[PDB]
Image (cartoon, rainbow over all chains, first blue to last red; front, side, top):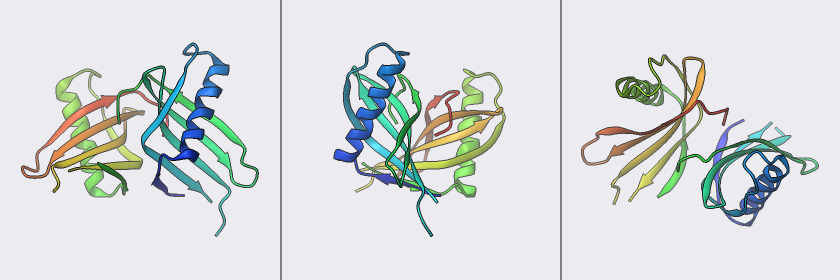
Length: 91
Length: 90
């Protein structure tokens, strides 16, 4: 579909927690501690009717910046961590 | 500083060629070949306006890279701030 910039309020912060919680189960970067999702946060609506969303997030965790992609199902709110890249520099 | 999504028409494609041209002169990645700027493309306004930062995902040499370009509002001069890669799809 197309991308938009979205706010970094509670919903986005929970996406960040999700990413870090998924990454913690993988273990690839040791144990990360969620800090905050920072600007900018990008959302892609995937389609007359939405079927899914893709999020790109910059997450501060363990004082370092990471880039996370998350897919979400519109119908059942099912989330998958597609990518977790980092430590990346600031956007 | 408020970010916005911008489209990927000729202007953005030229920014991508600029990024690759700049990075080729820097040399960190050897000789890259510009392919395409892909969605999403982001632009941040830095404040009266001082200038802009563009974040572009640039395909070059079959690989995806993240490029940040600064532009000064008064001078209209651009700089390559970051060239990060290869990164996965955004």
